[PDB]
Image (cartoon, rainbow, N blue to C red):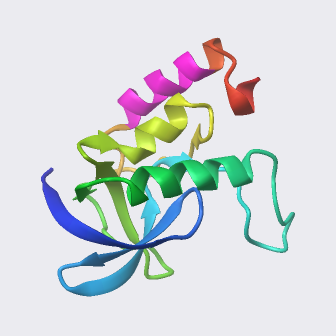
Amino acid sequence: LHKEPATLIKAIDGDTVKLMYKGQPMTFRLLLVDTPETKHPKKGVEKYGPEASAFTKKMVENAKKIEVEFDKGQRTDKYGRGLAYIYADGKMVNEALVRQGLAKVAYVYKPNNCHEQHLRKSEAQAKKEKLNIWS
């Protein structure tokens, strides 16, 4: 795996960000995590949805460097979204959300599972500390 540079365009939700990558706008979905959501007229807004969305927004808007890391399987999903691990100044946004109790580890589909072990470790700790969703 290798990290490549990208530029923020806009944060959309806890689990989705729009970036300029290789000179083109794309929507990215964060690999291996599921955050409560604010969109959708499904349930509309779920508990901890606004919080997860603000967490992601502040972490990417305040970064001096954004990097994307593709896994070793497919790189886009059926909606055209990029599938990746996103780093802000060297820290993985995906892991940060799970460590804070603002995401659960979710949808693990081989072979895009390279950091699965590491994120399950972070999720166990957040549950143990009874944070946010696990409160």
**SS majority, magenta:** helix
Image quarter of residue 81: bottom left
Q: Is residue 30 visible?
A: yes
Q: At 23% across and 68% down in the image, what residue appears?
A: 6
Find residue 102 and report its horizontal and vertical position in percent: 62, 39
Q: How many marks?
A: 0
Find residue 50 and report its horizontal and vertical position in percent: 71, 54
Q: At 76% across and 23% down in the image, what residue appears?
A: 135
Q: Is residue 114 visible?
A: no
- Magenta-drawn stretch contains 123: yes
Tell whether 75 sits left or right of 9: left
Question: From what the image shows, is residue 124 above or below residue 67?
Answer: above
Q: At 15% across and 50% down in the image, what residue appears?
A: 1
Find residue 74 and report its horizontal and vertical position in percent: 31, 67
Question: From which residue to which does the magenta span run?
Answer: 116-126
Give 61 or 50, whichever is nearer the viewer. 61
Find residue 40 and report its horizontal and vertical position in percent: 77, 72
In this view, which residue lies farthest toward the bottom?
A: 24
- Magenta-drawn stretch contains 114: no
Question: From what the image shows, is residue 126 above or below residue 30?
Answer: above
In this view, which residue lies farthest toward the top?
A: 128
